[PDB]
Image (cartoon, rainbow, N blue to C red):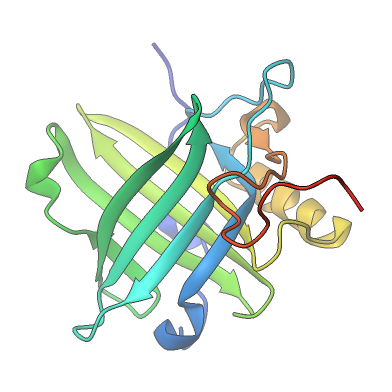
Length: 182
């Protein structure tokens, strides 16, 4: 029926002089907010990870990995550099039926600890957006998480559209294995 409209792009900061080489590698999804995302604590959202592999042509192979129904689930896609550094579009949008636009904007990052990334897309002439708080570890400070909430709210999202996924090991942590807790 209804979706919160996407915010104007002037309300979404862009990371100055984005460094594509330094953004590469594995990020954990510590916070996740969107107009089509609903926090649901009774069957809680598990953490997933996203690996940004920088190709020689400066696009990223982006692999999200999630533990879902006793298997690893993936969303592999390509981010092709967009209109400004730190912006991207989806590789072959034609392969996604009904998708008329896809935008990625890196909002803020220090590269070695945290990042915030904004995503906006139009599918079946309906406008979606999400914001992701990434960490190089599965935990970030309360200050970063409160900043994320403040930012997400400034983009028009109520609190029930903001998720802090629960840390897990399966699929996302490639050297944790299975052991009794220390």
